[PDB]
Image (cartoon, rainbow over all chains, first blue to last red; front, top):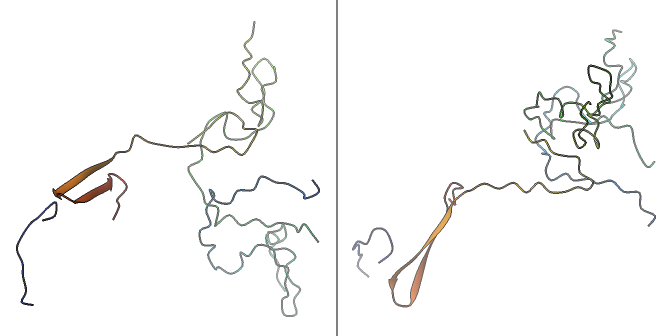
Length: 13
Length: 52
Length: 53
Length: 45
């Protein structure tokens, strides 16, 4: 989403 | 109209640590024990090396 | 009262590289080889152009 | 070393460079803008 490094990283909520 | 004026700016010229040695304050005559005191803080008599 | 003798401390107001050049060092009354009075003094040093003729 | 003509008044010596300061207006989304702000030689962090 931002300018440099887009990556998926999710925790359970 | 009355005030006395000098163009004094202290912002450019630095204010770094004046290192706490054995006597470098601005102007203190002060008092010594029984052997007489030093006249001024940075005057021409500390040049005269004196013993008691 | 009111003005005091001042033993001015310089450890605060620091020390820089000081120029070895003719029109910076000291602002005193000077001279040329022949004897014509050059003025490296504050307000007059190098503003005027005096050339011999 | 800076030597000048004698000054009548306490006048400022306005000292600059040709230093760079470039900003990219980043936009991955319709609605929000990322402001990539950096004075290049003078570290912003």
